[PDB]
Amino acid sequence: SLQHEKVTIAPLVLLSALDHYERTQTKENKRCVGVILGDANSSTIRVTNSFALPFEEDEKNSDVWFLDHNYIENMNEMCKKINAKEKLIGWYHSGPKLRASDLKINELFKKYTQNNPLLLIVDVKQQGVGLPTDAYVAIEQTEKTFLHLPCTIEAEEAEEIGVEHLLRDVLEVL
Amino acid sequence: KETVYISSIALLKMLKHGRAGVPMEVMGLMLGEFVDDYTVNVVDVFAMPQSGTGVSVEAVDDVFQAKMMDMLKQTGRDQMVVGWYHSHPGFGCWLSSVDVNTQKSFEQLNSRAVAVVVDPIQSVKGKVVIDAFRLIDLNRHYYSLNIDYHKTAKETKMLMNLHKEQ
Ligand SMILES: [Zn+2]
Image (cartoon, rainbow over all chains, first blue to last red; front, side, top):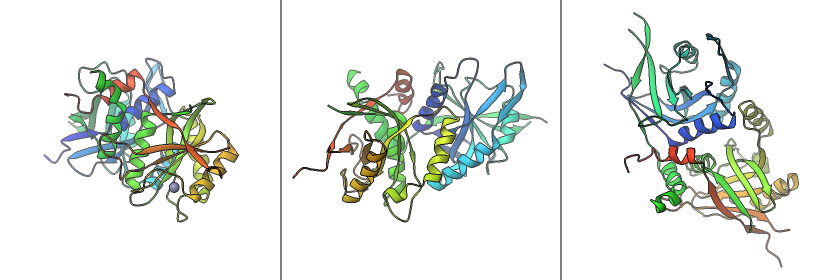
């Protein structure tokens, strides 16, 4: 096998997905959707940034949804001006679970990524047992299906410093 | 008596951006709310592109800024520009004469504006090197505000997944 083996996610991405969900006052059963950025050129996909997307879907019909293509292109172009190292590698949504339209939505992102797109579900409700993240890439089996990839949360030094600073008061208490 | 409250994503983006820019200075805008005369909430930031001019009022690309601000609105972030941040890689947190000029431009747009300065080189585990300034209204030109961090319970749980076993 040459397949991706695993995924690492920066704490900023987790917090960005949560902030997106909260700031749009997303209300159950709805989800928020966006783009993830990072590096998918090795067996370890590294997810290091993200941005929100305008997104709408029909409650009465899983087949009906809209993503703003122009928004993807225009925001990505600004992202590239800030840091070309963080490539468009996939998309995320707030889940908490895979949804029926996800393989079709994923086919759209395929037009924007160099890699086979990564779908990151970030469970912003955080009810899960373990990590609030599930990672998938689409594969054939003869039909398309999502392959579940293991995740870990990892940070570069800057963010590690940042997170430790943010949890200081909690750490003292505990 | 004055305090700048910095959110989790704002602090992480500023540290990330500063480190990515090394050895150059970087800059961006801070978004948030002026809560009262002694309180500024910084809920988010965004990076400005590197400019040949270096960090100054000239570095502010108004076309980039307008586009970025409009697109943030469309996805639920419609907070006021409450100031700006820039990095001082290796040389600590203060305002140079050019920084003071930049800040004066921000202050003229909104007298409550805050200048944050971060040092991505000297920031180390256990030590974030950051400060926040305003200009004074033989006197010195500027002064430092307290910085604190605001995080929700949801954010606290989310941050704890780093080193989750511990
Ligand atoms: Zn400066």
